[PDB]
Length: 66
Ligand SMILES: [Zn+2]
Ligand SMILES: [Zn+2]
Image (spheres, rainbow, N blue to C red):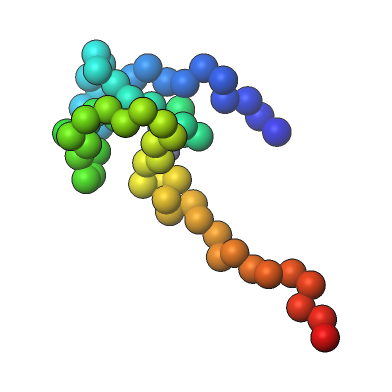
């Protein structure tokens, strides 16, 4: 189960703060230029880091009878 309400307000690249952006499902924080690829502007929605994109599992289709 665990819990992850309050996200981390500290970077994990240069250990610097200020204009930090924490991933949706990942409390981890990063800087615009630090991110790869770096973001030009702050997105207004659900942003996903590399970890999230790499956390994609093969979508299988159950019930394959007949
Ligand atoms: Zn950084
Ligand atoms: Zn993430």
